[PDB]
Length: 129
Ligand code: NA
Image 1 (cartoon, helix red, strand yellow):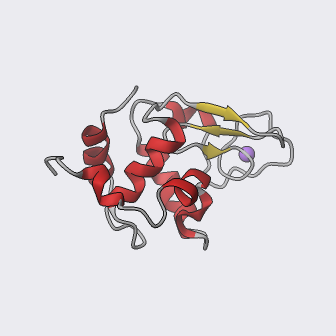
Image 2 (cartoon, helix red, strand yellow):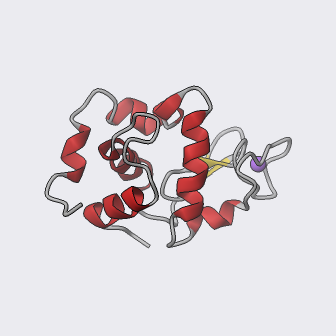
């Protein structure tokens, strides 16, 4: 599923991401935009053999099991395919665990490089929230 900007903002808010660990809603919408272009089916392979999955491009090395990343942890206790679902619950629930680990939203490369220090409120402007 390819979300609309405001439709994603409302689902993230419903799941409790607005101000989760001090990160306003605009940060999560910005990160989803640059990580997956709002597509729940997005996958990208890395050089180390790991794979990033879903709307928030959650990596198979630490967070999920895809059965092909040797010596990898499954810290969110889920199959990576659960992160490609049109329902974002698993992606949101796993993202809350990642953002809590100590590095905050810096775990998402595209957030650090394209959202961090910008006007992230613009990503929710015009939405009925
Ligand atoms: Na894994």
